[PDB]
Length: 251
Length: 260
Image (cartoon, rainbow over all chains, first blue to last red; front, side, top):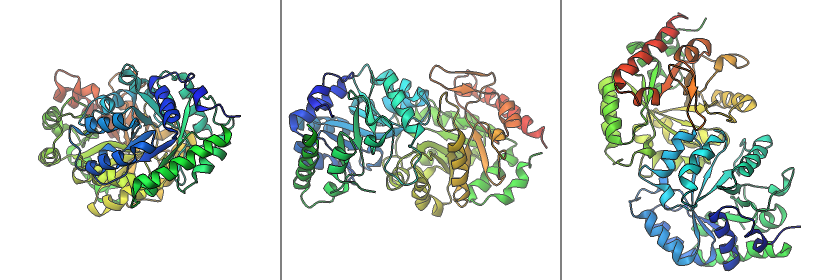
């Protein structure tokens, strides 16, 4: 039994988490673009082209050699135009006091333009306390890295289970998880008020159908197959339909 | 018994690791300043004031709102003037392909100006390969986060032991660890070719409001077997940072001298 996204909108405890479900339902999409292109100019261009097909655009702001102070406002304009959220894949991983400054300040001022960020739990739950200090008043959401797609990683077992307990102690701010196979967690994907987003999706790589329908995730994160396409809008539509149909099979 | 730093120079398998031991003995310091001030202008000023006292200046370049592309050169000039290494505490924690870009590229171009960076092992051992690809040809070194000073952290037990084994497989690049209590590990601090640098250091035990836990210089170096004390707020929130830094230097060096 899977609750439909429309029943989970009312369960989400954070305003960004609620918005994410609302976008998915309105646009019939559970697709996140991993916008791993060479420059900010290419990022804004591909965000505009694939915007109709996505619920979320995932960025690495610290890879862009042409970052400028207006990058965030230009990307926010595109997100508002096409109705998607911006997720900065910053993987915060420091002590609580440091991450406050890495999130709110510096050159990137991530808090001002990213709806969602993610964090590892390795430094302990103080990382959540530090990101929440400036994130929660702004209405932002946090995803915890409970599992990862890379070889030999340590986000497994008791570590994954600890991420679930941290999320449930901080659900004013933690909207969900980065996860790989939450169906195979001891308790499964767990509380439907929290959302799962899964990297490594491709038509190691797993198919949209496997990720959504077999593995119990909620959002597919897709990069290379769209980024490298001759026609990214056309390929993004294919991924949206695959991920959405996989969800509908249960819902 | 522990080896004097000068006797470990010959064991270092990476040139930045070797240089770090050489600086510590030249200057009689095992102090690293965590220069977590509000601006790059203030960072460069404090690095110049405290530089005589330190073997390494640790930065968080992503907290500086006035960062510009001349930062690396300006900080390297101070590092040369006062003979210290630059450690960017970026805590890389992504997959290999992404970390390569976050190290060599973007706006910060960390590889251009940081002698040392650090990485978490949580994403798997491939993170080391990702950073080594462009760091090793430039002679850079890497510290692995085997433990942390923050409350409730997960860098413990089998995770710490895995970081030790990953380091063993990458002696060309991994110069040592961020660690907290290496004397407590099954075989102690381990291979003396590797260095241990410990955050969470203040003259009095205590903590902050967001999970930081502080131990004294003497306990870190002498009791817990580390090699380097990393001190941030203990120095940078002082009215006279240079004088406070000299107090920490003397405590950490004397703690090490007790074992020589």
